[PDB]
Every structure is written in C-alpha cells, then in structure tokens.
C-alpha cells in the first residue's frame, strides 16, 4: 500500500496490539500493584515472569522471541521500566509499566488522529452511526461505504466536530494517514456523494509474533376567511373580563385567527364563559382579526385591567 | 396515679367497662388534648408492673398508633409501630415505618428499612413510591421505568416517574414526556402535571410553553401563585407581580404555621418557599435599579451560603436568580453549585453544569486543549475529570495548563494587573498541589517521582506562601523521602562510604522538612498535632547533627509555646536521650514551658522525679530545681500530694 | 486518650459527621507512678454486666441461663470441636429471646421521645467505637469493660489493657472477633437491624479516618516506638524493633483497606461489610472465652 | 402615634441610605428587637416588622444577625402563632 500504509499502519497496528495485550494482561492479573520492602510500585508486571505468560499463550516461542517482541514495544515507547529505564527489554524480575498507564504517555499528532479514527470506528460499528452499508459508485460495490457528504453531516449532528470546516480538514489528515480512503481513486475528502472505505479496522487485531416543543390543541386547521363570511358556522359574542390579582388566566396561540389556547377553569374568565375552543377578532374595541398572537398579547398587557374581548364561539360545528 | 390505684382495685368487670369507654373516646370524637392525656396514660401503664391495658386485643397496638399519628407524637408512633413489626413483618408496616422516620428527621433509619425489604421480600414488594420518600431518585427512576414498561401506562405511574425526573433535573426528557401526552390525559392529572411541566419548560427557557402550563395550575395552590408571578416578571408586569406574591405568602400561611408548630426542622421546607419569594422581590429592584446591582449580587452570594447544602434546594434558588442573571455574569455561584453536585455523587449534572459554563464540550474535542479563558472554571473541570476516572487525560491537561498559566502570567504581567497576577499565582499553587498528589497516585513511590513532586510543591510554596496546604504537603513529602532512603540503606547495607553519602543525602531533605513543619504549624494554629509529632520524630532521630539542630533552634524560638502542650507526654519520654545536643535543647524547651503554664508540667514531672532509673529522675529534678524558683509552692504541694496519694493507693 | 482527642477533632471538622454529632466519650487519665495513677470517674454510668444482671433478677430470669442451657445439652462444651460448638451456641440462641438490653432501655427511659433520642446516640456511639477499636486493635471487650451512660445513652469503653490484636496472638482463649457486635447489642438498635444507622455511621467514620490516615499514623508511630511501652509487645511475643515494624504495617493495611488481602485494595463500603460478617459469624463467636459472654 | 411615625421614617431612610447606614445597623437592631418582643410597646408590630424588613433588605444584613440575636427565629415564629392581622 506504499509508504503511507507501510509506516503509519504498522505504527498503528503495534499500538492496537499493545492495547489488546494490556487488556488481556489485566484480566490475567499479570499487571498488579507491588510493594518492595515498604516501597510501593503500582500497576507493575515483572519482566521475567511475563515471558512465561507469553509462552503459555503461544505469542512467544522462547525467551529470545519474547525479548525481541518486547524490545520492539520499547523502541516505540509503549512500555517503560518503572524505575530508571533499562532500554532493551531484559529477562529479570524488574517492574515495568505501559505508556498508556500514564507513566509517560508520549502523545503525537499521528497518535491523536489514529485514536480519534479508532473511536470513530467504534461509533461506525455501533448502530448509532449506520452509514456503513454496501453501496455502488463508479460501477463497483464496496462494503463499509458511506457518502462523504453524509459523513460531514453526521459529524456536525453527532458533535464530534461541530464546525464543518474543522470536520472536513480532520478527514484530510486521516486520508493522508490512510485511515479513510475514497473507494475508487482515493479522491480527497469533499462534501459530495464520494463513497469512502475505512482502510483501518479496529476489530480483529494483529498478533505479537506478526509485528415537538410547541403544543397545539385546536382541531380547526384554519379559519381565515371562514369567519369573515357572515352567518353560518358561528355566532359572535362579546366577553368583558375584569382584571384579577392572580391575572386573567387565558392564553391565545392562533397565528392568523388568534384562537384561545387555554383558559384557567378557576379564573374569572371561565366563570364568564370563555371556553377553550374559541376565536377572537377584537380586543378592548380594537379589531385584531389579522395579527400575530404575540402582538395581541402585547395589546392585552398594555391595556386596562378590564379587557373587552369578542369570542367567535363556534356552535358545535 | 389515680388511674393505676383505681384500675388495680377493679375486679376485671369494671376494667372492661372502663376500657370500652376509653376505646369510644379515642375512636370517636377524638380531641388532641384528651388523646395526648390518654396516650401518656398508656405509656405510664407500660412502665407499670401491671402491664399495658388490654383494649380490643394486642393492647391496642393499631389504635394507639393511629391516635399518636394524629397527635403528631411521632416517637410514640414509632415505638408502637415497632411492637407490631416484632409480631410480624408486613409491607404495609414497612411503608408506615418509613414515613414515620422521615417525619422524625431520621433518614438513616428509614434507609435501613429499605435494606430489610430488599433481603426478606425481594423487589416486587418494594414500591417505587418508597424510593421517592427516601429521595432515592436514581433507584426510583429504575423502579418507575421497570413498572411503566410492563404495566400499561397509568396516570399514577406517569406522575411518579415525572416527579422523579424533576428532582434529578433531567429537563430534556421531562419536556419530551409532557409534549407527547397532553390530550391523552384527564383534567385531574392535568393539574398535577403542569407544576412539573412548567419547571421543565422554565429549565429549557421556552417561555411560550411555560405560559400555557402555568394557567393550568390551580390558583389556590401556593406554588401556582408563585409560578404566575414569574411570568409577570418575564413580561415586566411589576405591579401585578407584587400582587401575586402577596397572595402567595397568604397561601403559605397554612403550611408555615402547621410545620412551625412541630419543630423547626419540618418548617425548613416552608422556609425555602419564603426565601424564593423574597428573592423574587429583589429581582424587581434588579430590573429597575442599575445602581443597586452589585449590592444585590453580594447579598445573593451571602444569602446562599447560609442556606443548607441540599442540591434540590439550591437548584430551586438558582433558577429564580437565573431569571435576570445569566450564569456567565456570576461564575462563583454555579461553581460552588457544581461542587455540591460532585460531593453528592451526581457528577452527570455537575458535568452538564460545567460544560454550560466552559462553553464547549471538552470530551468531544479530545485533541484540542482545554480553553484557557476562565481558568478557575477549567480547574474545576479537571478535578471533576479526575473523579470521573479519566485521570490520564486530567494529568496531561494539568501539565499543559500550567505551561499556559505561567506563560499567560509572564506575558501579561504589567503594573496595572496586580490583583489578576495575584489570583493567577493562587490558582497555579492549587494546580501544583494536584500535580503532586496525582503523580503519586499515577506513578507511585520510587527514585524518580520524589525529585519531581518536590519540584512541584516547591513551586506551589513560592506562589502561595501563606497557604497551609502547600507547606504541609511539601513537608510531608520531604519527611517520607528521608524515611525511604533510610530503609534503602537497611535493605542493602545491613542485609562506610554509603552512610557518609547518605548523610549529605538525608540532610539535603531534612532541613526543608524542619522549616516546612514549623511554618505549617503556625499556619494551622490549632490543628498542628500531626505536624508537631512529625517534628519530634525528626528531632529525636537526626537532631544530634549540627545542621538539623540549628534549624530547630530557630524554629523553637519562632513556634508558639502553646503548641508544645499537646506533646508534653512525648517530650518527657525522651528526657534522658544519650545525645547531648538533643537533651540540652529539650531542657531549654521545657524551661520555657515551665515559665508559662507550669500546671501543664508538674504532674508528669513529679512522676519522672521519683523514677527508679537514675538518669530520668536526675534530669527531672534538675528541671524541677529551675521550676521551683518561679513558684516553689506548686512543687512542694504536688510532691506531697502525689506521695500521699501513692501511699493511699497501695497500703 | 491523646488518640481519641485527634479523632474527635477530625469528626468535628467533617460536616457530615458533625451533623450526626459523632464523637468518642473520653475521660481524664493521670499517671502517678509505674503502678498507680488517677482515672477520671465518669458519672451516670454502669457496666453492661450489671444492667443485665439486675434486669434478669427483677424479671426472675436466671443470670447464667445461656451457659446452663449449653452445659445441659452438651456438658463437654469446652472440649468440643468447632462445628459442635456452633451447634451448641445456636441451640442456646434459638431458645433464648435476646432482647434484654432493648427491653430495659425502654423501661428505664422516662418517655418515648427521650427513649428515641437515647437510642440514636447509643447506635452511633457504638459504631464509632467499633471502627476506632478495630484500627487501634482493641480486644477483650467483655461486658464488664464497657459501660452505658443512663442519660445520654452513649456507650463508653474503659480499661484498654489489650491493644494491637494481643488477644488474637495469645494461645490461650484466642479472640477472633475484631469488635463486639453481639446479638443483644443488635437488638437494642433499630428493629430493622445493623443495615440502618450502624452501617451508615461506620461508612462515615471509615471515610474520615482513611482521608486523614497520615494524622492517625503519626500518633500511632510515636507511642508504639517508645522503649518504655515496648514491654507490652515483648510480652505478646512468645527482635523488639522488628516486632514493632510488623504492627505498624498491619495498622496501615487496615487504613488502606488491604488488611484482608494485601494484593487487592478494598473500597470503604466493601471493607465495612466484611468486618460485620467477621464480628457476627457464629463460628468466630463460639471460640471466644465464655467470660466474654458471646451469647449476650 | 409618635413612635409609629418615627418608625415609618426610619424605614424610608433604609432604602434611601444605600449601604451608608451599616455602621448603625447593630444599634437599631438591638433597639427594634427590644421593641419587637412583648406587646407592651405602644408601637404597632406591623410597622415594627415592616421597617425591620427595609433594613435587612437595603443594608443586606443576612445570616449574621442570627448569630447576634439567637431568639430572632423564636420571635418570628411566635408571631405566626399569635398575630391575627394578615398584613
Ligand atoms: O473538594 P476539594 O477537591 O477538596 O476542593 C476544595 C473545596 O473546593 P470546591 O469549592 O471546588 O469544592 C473547598 O471548598 P468547600 O466546599 O470546603 O467550601 C475549597 O475551600 P474554600 O471554600 O475555602 O475556597 C478548597 O480550596 P483551598 O485549597 O484553596 O482551601 C478546595 O481545595 P482544592 O482546590 O485544593 O481542591
């Protein structure tokens, strides 16, 4: 796959295997806190004993192979001696700790891109991001195909990169690393239909030896011009409501007709009729047949304590 | 006494006539005063040899419990309800037992009742309402979720789960459940919904929805009047707001009076309602008087710290002030709030709070470093992140943060910003301290960490001299290093040149320790026991060296003489230390303890003065000879009294 | 008593503990010689053994009823095997209502309102001294060595002659019980059991002590290392410096929570639960010397 | 009626003072608490309680008065059991 695959992926692969190894070792209890004659050492694993563990699991055939594999990890920095570093791995009862255990944790730009890509792949594997599907572009069907335009939308929606420009730039870095490659010609990431394939897959790691807010209660959809026509469905009525210490207790939430949204059953309005299924066209004399509900809400508050209101009062139709 | 005298004479037939009449009085036309008289009679009869009066079987364990409950004699209720429990355990009994404990302000006892239910009855018998009473909102939600999945949706189980959501504060999920179910609901549950639905809308800041819900709340409810008054202040209806608040206070009459009658603790709930009411009065001024604003903030800050540290109460209070004060305009309020959420074990809400203050999501921007703007906020996030078991990130951020801080300090240090510069040093100091404690938890104790964590604590000490924790932590670090190196010699040398090198090495770490402990003693000024004992351990072991003695001499002068009274026993134990330079300074120290507060010294000294071994009694007498000159009367009195008491003690 | 002063300071500083009014009842101790000294007399106190004796004579109950039941069923109790002892002990417990202390706390109290307050203090004070006694290592807690305040209701421990697990070390009548958590004390608490006030109080006390482990360690190290007080450790043994090192390490493990297993650290809730099981285990209780009264 | 009009004036000064009366707050608080307790005082409790409100409000004396005057919480819960006027 060229220099890009041979270098970056190999670095990625050893890190993925090292992480797989660390999780396995913790389950096997190889890495455990130790105290040497009242001198503690947390999250430690003895170098000499580890070789035996590797032989049992068949990762390393003999002492040579185990040392070589661990030396490769040391040349990367995935592990470090708890005390002053001994550099090349040695078959001695000595305490070592992983970099990812925060002992040193040397970060780099490649690692951050790799780690983010790995985390994204877990999201892509999960149902949460189901963009991965078999799809055909340029006459060829490939698995794990997700449109580049769809991916950019998903990043903003998911919140991994809220800014589209930042999201698109991040993919270019991954494309340079090779984490994501366009299916056919490795075309650089663009907000287009361009189908992409994930070259790096976290699963099946390598082996050591191989290294609705609003509410609407009005049934009538629209009454504009339905009311204006004289007679027929409704009979007009005028309601005069007196102010109260606790307020009138009614809400109007009709865009054009300004229908009454709700009425307080214990309030003065409910005592003087004022049922929920009503429409208003004039308040305190002024005709408000065609205005917004909020504008009417401004007028009723700015008006006097006693409000003159006209209710359409549909007759059960 | 009259009753017992009579009740003994009666030949059982008259006792039944009496007991039947007692039943009628309790059962029918019960009067509080008569009841508590007859309850005190039943308790008095329990203490009597005759035994409790047998009424309608079981000694009226059910009736007297019901009667004590109406009398609000919750201790009598508990005792009687426990007698019934002893005969048999029932779910009904457990429920009443729980409610009794909550009324009695004994939360721990009620929690134990739930543990009994878990073991002996399992899970089905535990209703979700039981968690609700115990304020186990996390476990109540699990119960209401399990119940509402299997059983068909019911008004009661819906309100129960919604009530839990508002206590947790999950306003997102609570507002979705509201919008979904309005027409599906009856008008009775509708009125029980809006009080919780409005809270959710208010939390999200959607004022149109909030107006719809508040109208559905009954006016008669005290809470409903307050909610209406809130939509007044949103619409700037100041005149109507004051009217609504007054009616709200009027409705709180009944609640405040009833709770105040039986202990202050029950009245606390009502007290919080008036707290929020009078704060709403101080929002009208805040919206009218720009000149009064900074006073209001100081008042608000001082008031909230007097209030109790319960997270529910704070959320209520903060929501009120948030009507006219965005969280950015007052950071310290919401940070202290987040800390309570952290301490109470609800870091999810704490996290949301901190994200809202930060501005962005740090977790999403893993590669990006934490924002520097508002550093006090950032620091709170890191120490939260540590509690969230993301230490690897937190530690790395702290290293980056201090580099930014120290660069932001250097470049921005002008003569003008001196308060800013001083605050930055105080922050960095708290950062440096976290580094050390974290490094030990992450790395461990070994040859490489100790020089590093010392570098950090040293910087912390520089940036905040007066701060107690910076000196104590630095001192304790140095002392541990001295012990660790000594053990290394024992492990390798015991099991010529190395001890002479160790002399320079330990003295390199010993002189810092002495200076630090003496400064950390003065700073604590009343909590220096640990520090003072550590001084003694160091003094006795290594003080025979000239350099360690020198530091101690200046320290013993500097330190106050009241501190040494704590450790008078430990001093006299080593009165005869073979090392001369130690013993000579002990005498000089005891001398000054003698000259002021001799009553603290005479008793242990008199015991040493008559010790069998010569060196102890010789030293003790030499000190007493000097003590005598000041008073002499005490020495003669105590020497006689003690000799006579010994004679008395063993003939 | 210097140690108790330190712990009381720590409890005062913690707000949760302060709200619960947790504290250790302590008294003045003034030595006068190697033999003699003055102890401050605590008023309104009486030994637990006296209370049970006087209650059982009033109610005409035999004072040695539990012992008599055992010797009746199996007169060779002392020489029986462990399993046999467990049976014998259980047979006594099933045929005796172990409610004497709870019942007498009621009768003694003037009124229910006071009674409830006395019991709350009682439960918390016991939990506080259970955890502190475990760390300090205080053994040999037979009912003659603890007395109960008849007004405040708080428990008081006296005569700390045995410390640092001396009782466990001695071959004769070895004590395997870390702290006294017998059934009668449990009955005296809330009806539900140890799950309530006792367990919650133990969690709070353990958390505070673990947080301030350095302060506790400093006090312990100074007096233990003193040559004058070294004699007690030497008597327990069967040199002296080596013995002291082990004792400090054992105490450190308890504070960390590694006492049960050095390899695995234990959280405060888990460690407390394991301690309760050891105290309440029937097998451990049976071994205890009969004078300790494992059946009260 | 003389003391009643003096209290209504002190209450109006409270708001106008704008934190310049803090030095005198402990003096007026003692005086008023002397007048709050008992019904012997001619001055109406209503205006007594009202002016105390204006002082606490404007000057910002919160929580700290509780330490100085421990009976304050017992005094204010006694009016709720005694007073019949709503205001
Ligand atoms: O909970 P901690 O991690 O130990 O942090 C505490 C805590 O700060 P928070 O407000 O963030 O919780 C203290 O506040 P309290 O809750 O005890 O009131 C605060 O003390 P102050 O209130 O006096 O500022 C103290 O700060 P400091 O170390 O300056 O005394 C600070 O400690 P750390 O910042 O070192 O964690």
Image: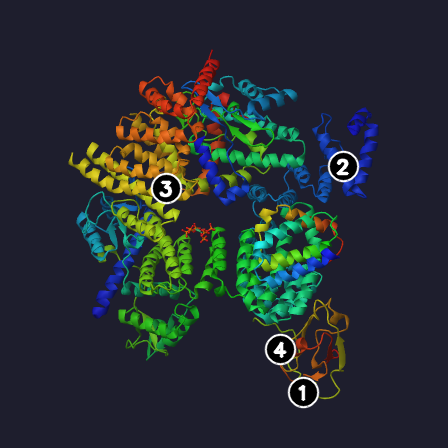
Residue at the disc numbered 1: A225
Quadrant the N terminus of chain A occupies: bottom left
Chain identity of mark 2: B
* Residue A294, disc: 4
Chain identity of mark 3: C
Chain identity of mark 1: A
| Separation (CA) of disc 2 from disc 1 | 76 Å
Work out whether disc 2 and disc 4 sit on a shared chain.
Answer: no
Work out whether disc 2 and disc 1 sit on a shared chain.
Answer: no
Neighbour tally class for label 4: few under 14, some 14-19, many 20 plus, Cα within 10 Å? some
Q: Is residue A98 left or right of residue C6?
A: left
Comparing C292 with C211, the one in front is C211
Q: Is residue A167 visible?
A: yes
Quadrant the C terminus of chain A occupies: bottom right
Work out whether disc 3 and disc 4 sit on a shared chain.
Answer: no
Residue at disc 4, secondary structure = helix
**Residue contact at pointers 3 and 4, CB within 8 angstroms:** no
- The mark closer to the camera, 2 or 1, is 2
Q: How many marks?
A: 4
Chain identity of mark 4: A
| Separation (CA) of disc 2 from disc 4 | 63 Å
* Residue A30 position within the rendered picture, expressed as x and y whole percent measured from the top left: 30, 46
Q: Is residue C81 left or right of residue B8?
A: left
Residue at disc 1, secondary structure = loop
């Amino acid at each position: 796959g060229g220099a890009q695959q041979r270098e970056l992926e190999r670095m990625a692969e050893v890190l993925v295997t090292g992480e797989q190894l660390r999780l396995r070792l913790h389950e096997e209890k190889v890495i455990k806190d130790r105290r040497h004659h009242l001198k503690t050492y947390p999250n430690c694993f003895v170098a000499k004993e580890l070789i035996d563990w590797l032989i049992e699991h068949k990762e390393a055939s003999d002492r040579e192979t185990a040392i070589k594999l661990m030396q490769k990890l040391a040349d990367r920095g995935i592990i470090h001696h708890v005390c002053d570093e001994h550099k090349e791995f040695k078959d001695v009862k000595l305490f070592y700790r992983f970099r990812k255990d925060d002992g040193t944790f040397p970060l780099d730009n490649e690692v951050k891109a790799f780690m983010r890509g790995q985390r994204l792949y877990e999201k892509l594997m999960s149902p949460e991001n189901t963009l991965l599907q078999p799809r055909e572009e340029e006459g060829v069907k490939y698995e794990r195909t997700f449109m580049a335009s769809e991916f950019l939308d998903w990043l903003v929606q998911e919140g991994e990169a809220t800014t589209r420009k930042e999201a698109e730039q991040l993919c270019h870095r991954l494309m340079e690393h090779g984490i994501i490659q366009h299916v056919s010609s490795k075309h650089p990431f663009v907000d287009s239909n361009l189908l992409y394939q994930f070259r790096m897959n976290f699963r099946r790691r390598r082996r050591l030896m191989e290294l609705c807010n609003p509410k609407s209660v009005l049934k009538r959809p629209v009454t504009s011009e339905e009311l204006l026509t004289p007679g027929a469905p409704y009979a007009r009525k005028t309601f005069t409501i007196v102010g109260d210490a606790v307020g009138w207790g009614f809400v109007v939430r009709g865009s054009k007709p300004c229908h009454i949204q709700a009425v307080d059953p214990s309030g003065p309005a409910a005592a003087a009729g004022m049922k929920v299924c009503q429409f208003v066209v004039s308040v305190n004399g002024l005709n408000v047949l065609h205005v917004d509900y909020r504008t009417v809400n401004n007028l009723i508050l700015t008006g006097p304590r006693t409000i003159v209101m006209e209710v359409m009062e549909e007759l059960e139709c | 006494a009259a009753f017992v005298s009579c009740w003994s004479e009666l030949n059982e037939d008259q006792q039944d006539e009496l007991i039947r009449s007692i039943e009628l009085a309790l059962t029918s036309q019960d009067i509080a005063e008569v009841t508590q008289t007859l309850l005190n009679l039943a308790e008095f009869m329990e203490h009597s040899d005759k035994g409790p009066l047998p009424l309608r079987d079981d000694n009226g364990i059910v009736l007297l419990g019901e009667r004590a409950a109406k009398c609000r004699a919750y201790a009598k209720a508990l005792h009687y309800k426990e007698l019934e429990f002893q005969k048999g355990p029932t779910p009904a009994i457990l429920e009443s037992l729980i409610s009794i404990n909550n009324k009695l302000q004994q939360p721990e006892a009620a929690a134990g009742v739930l543990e009994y239910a878990m073991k002996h009855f399992g899970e089905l018998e535990i209703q979700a309402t039981w968690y609700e009473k115990l304020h186990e909102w996390e476990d109540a939600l699990v119960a209401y979720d399990k119940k509402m999945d299997t059983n068909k949706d019911d008004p009661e189980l819906m309100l129960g789960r919604m009530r839990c959501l508002e206590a947790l504060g999950e306003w997102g999920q609570l507002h979705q459940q509201c919008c979904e179910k309005w027409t599906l609901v009856n008008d009775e549950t509708q009125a029980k919904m809006a009080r919780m639905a409005a809270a959710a809308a208010w939390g999200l800041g959607q004022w149109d929805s909030m107006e719809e819900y508040t109208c559905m709340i009954p006016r008669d409810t005290h809470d409903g009047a307050f909610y209406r008054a809130v939509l007044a202040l949103h619409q700037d209806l100041f005149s109507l707001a004051q009217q609504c608040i007054d009616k709200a206070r009027d409705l709180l009459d009944a609640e405040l009076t009833a709770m105040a009658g039986e202990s202050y603790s029950r009245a606390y709930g009502a007290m919080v309602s008036c707290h929020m009411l009078s704060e709403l009065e101080e929002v009208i001024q805040y919206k009218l008087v720009p000149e009064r604003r900074e006073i209001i903030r100081q008042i608000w800050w001082e008031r909230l710290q007097g209030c109790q540290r319960i997270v529910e109460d704070w959320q209520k209070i903060l929501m009120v002030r948030s009507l006219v004060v965005s969280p950015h305009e007052d950071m310290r309020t919401w940070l202290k709030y987040a800390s309570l959420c952290g301490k109470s074990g609800r870091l999810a809400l704490a996290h949301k709070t901190l994200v809202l203050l930060l501005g962005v999501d740090p977790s999403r921007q893993l590669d990006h470093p934490l924002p520097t703007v508002h550093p006090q906020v950032t620091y709170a996030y890191m120490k939260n992140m540590w509690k969230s078991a993301r230490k690897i990130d937190a530690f790395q951020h702290m290293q980056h943060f201090v580099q930014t801080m120290q660069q932001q300090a250097q470049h921005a240090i002008a003569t003008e910003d001196q308060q800013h510069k001083q605050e930055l040093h105080k922050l960095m100091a708290r950062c440096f301290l976290k580094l050390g404690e974290w490094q030990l938890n992450l790395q461990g104790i070994n040859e490489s960490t100790i020089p590093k964590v010392l570098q950090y604590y040293s910087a912390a000490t520089e940036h905040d001299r007066s701060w107690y924790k910076a000196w104590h932590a630095w001192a304790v670090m140095n002392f541990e290093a001295v012990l660790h190196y000594k053990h290394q010699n024992q492990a390798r040398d015991e099991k010529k040149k190395v001890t002479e090198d160790l002399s320079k090495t330990l003295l390199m770490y010993t002189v810092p320790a002495v200076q630090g402990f003496f400064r950390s003693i003065s700073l604590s000024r009343g909590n220096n026991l640990q520090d003072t004992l550590r001084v003694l351990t160091l003094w006795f072991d290594y003080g025979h060296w000239p350099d360690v003695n020198e530091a101690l001499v200046e320290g013993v002068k500097a330190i106050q003489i009241d501190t040494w009274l704590q450790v008078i026993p430990q001093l006299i134990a080593r009165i005869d230390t073979p090392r001369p330079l130690v013993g000579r300074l002990i005498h000089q120290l005891l001398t000054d303890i003698g000259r002021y507060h001799p009553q603290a010294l005479i008793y242990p000294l008199t015991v040493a003065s008559k010790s069998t071994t010569t060196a102890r009694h010789n030293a003790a007498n030499k000190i007493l000879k000097n003590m005598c000159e000041h008073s002499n009367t005490l020495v003669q009195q105590a020497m006689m009294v003690s000799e006579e008491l010994i004679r008395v003690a063993i003939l | 008593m210097q140690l108790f002063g330190l712990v009381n300071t720590l409890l005062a500083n913690d707000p949760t503990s302060l709200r619960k009014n947790l504290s250790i009842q302590r008294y003045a101790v003034i030595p006068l010689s190697t033999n003699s000294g003055l102890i401050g007399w605590v008023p309104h106190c009486d030994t637990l053994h006296a209370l049970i004796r006087d209650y059982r004579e009033k109610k005409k109950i035999l004072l040695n009823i539990e012992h008599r039941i055992m010797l009746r069923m199996a007169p060779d109790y002392d020489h029986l095997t462990l399993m046999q002892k467990v049976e014998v002990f259980e047979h006594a417990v099933n045929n005796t209502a172990g409610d004497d202390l709870a019942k007498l706390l009621w009768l003694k109290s003037p009124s229910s309102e006071v009674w409830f307050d006395r019991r709350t203090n009682y439960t918390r004070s016991l939990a506080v001294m259970s955890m502190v006694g475990y760390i300090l290592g205080l053994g040999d807690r037979h009912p003659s060595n603890l007395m109960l305040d008849r007004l405040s209701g708080k428990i008081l421990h006296i005569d700390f002659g045995d410390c640092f697990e001396v009782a466990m070390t001695r071959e004769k009548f070895p004590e395997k019980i870390p702290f006294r958590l017998t059934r009668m004390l449990t009955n005296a608490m809330e009806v539900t059991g140890l799950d309530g006030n006792y367990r919650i109080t133990c969690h709070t006390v353990m958390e505070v002590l673990r947080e301030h482990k350095d302060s506790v360690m400093a006090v312990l190290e100074a007096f233990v290392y003193d040559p004058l007080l070294n004699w007690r450790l030497m008597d327990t043994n069967t040199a002296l410096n080596k013995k002291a090192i082990q004792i400090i390490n054992r105490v450190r493990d308890k504070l960390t929570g590694r006492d049960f297993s050095h390899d695995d650290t234990l959280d405060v809730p888990t460690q407390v639960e394991l301690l309760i099981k050891q105290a309440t285990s029937h097998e451990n209780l049976c071994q205890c010397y009969i004078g300790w009264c494992p059946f009260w | 009626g003389v003391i009643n009009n003096v209290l209504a004036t002190i209450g109006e000064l409270a708001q106008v003072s704008g934190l310049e009366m803090r030095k005198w707050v402990d003096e007026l608080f003692i005086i008023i608490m002397d007048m709050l307790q008992d019904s012997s005082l001619l001055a109406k409790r209503q205006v007594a309680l009202w002016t105390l409100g204006q002082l606490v409000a404007s000057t910002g004396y919160v929580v700290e008065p509780y330490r100085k005057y421990p009976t304050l919480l017992e005094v204010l819960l006694n009016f709720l059991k005694t007073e019949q006027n709503q205001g």
